[PDB]
Amino acid sequence: MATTLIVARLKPGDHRDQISRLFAESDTTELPDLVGVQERRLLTFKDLYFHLVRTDEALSKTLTPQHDHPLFRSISEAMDEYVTPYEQASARQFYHWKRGLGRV
Amino acid sequence: ATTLIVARLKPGDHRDQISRLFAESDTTELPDLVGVQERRLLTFKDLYFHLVRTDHPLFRSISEAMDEYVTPYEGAWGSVEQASARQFYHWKRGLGRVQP
């Protein structure tokens, strides 16, 4: 398993319905199956956008493509209408505790 | 329930100190009281994130210690408005749609 928190800045407005739709439609395709997604959450706080995604290496075969898959290109460019880089867009984890493991 | 708390980092590198705080906290009965299943602390640029999947002195002691290291992301109502993000989408393999 791996969990990644992706962060960006929202552009002015309320884009949540639009962003939600982009991901909902994507998640009906085989794209989460190519990636190996186990669970996805999207959140907002003030002008911040958060994409929290848990992936699993065993769920899919590894691809190392030279170019973006068209489905990834589509959602990536579509999201550019609603978010901009805050200023690598993944947060860096420095502490992990889990019930039954203690500190990981 | 998954909660994401956001704050702004004060200048410096406080990861060692923040880790020490939660290392001490997560040895107490606190995660048993809250029902914590998992906790992740992360940084991005000048941002601090506390991600938890689930006054009292155990809670208050970690609030008081974090003052050395973080400031509210927005100051106008800093400390009295919620610092937790609002989830608007959730998909889970097996069920598919969870929200909405």
Image (cartoon, coloured by chain):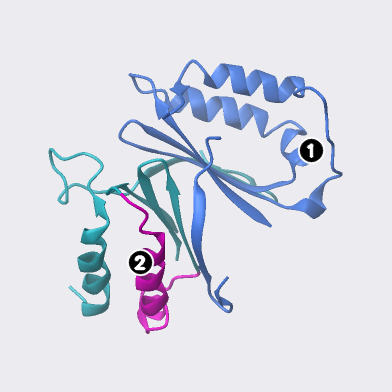
Chain colours: A blue, B cyan
Circle 2 — which element? helix
Foreground mark, 2 or 1? 2
**Residue appearing at x 62%, y 23% in the figure:** A75
Q: CA distance from mark 2 to mark 1?
A: 39 Å
- Percent across and percent down for residue A30 are 77, 34
Q: Up-down: is A6 above or below B61?
A: above
Please identify the quadrant where the N terminus of chain B is shown: bottom left
- Percent across and percent down for residue A31 are 74, 33
Give me the chain letter of mark 1.
Answer: A
Main SS class of the magenta portion in the image: helix
- Give the left or right position of residue A2, taking residue A16 as reference: right
Circle 1 — which element? helix
Question: As shown in the figure, which amino acid type bears the numbered disc 2?
Answer: Gln
On the image, numbered disc 1 is attached to which residue? A34
On the image, numbered disc 2 is attached to which residue? B17
- Percent across and percent down for residue B14 are 35, 58
Magenta highlight range? B12-37
Query: Do pointers 2 and 1 mark residues of a single chain?
Result: no
Question: As shown in the figure, which amino acid type bears the numbered disc 1?
Answer: Leu
Q: Residue B35 lies in magenta, yes or no?
A: yes
- Give the left or right position of residue A31, taking residue A48 as reference: right
Q: Up-down: is A24 above or below A94?
A: above
- Percent across and percent down for residue B44 are 44, 43
- Give the left or right position of residue A68, taking residue B11 as reference: right
Q: Would you call the spot at circle 2 few (<14 residues within 10 Å), some (14-19), or many (20 or more)?
A: some
- Give the left or right position of residue A63, taking residue A91 as reference: right
Give me the chain letter of mark 2.
Answer: B
**Residue appearing at x 41%, y 65% in the figure:** B16
> CB of mark 2 within 8 Å of CB of mark 1?
no
**Residue appearing at x 36%, y 64% in the figure:** B18
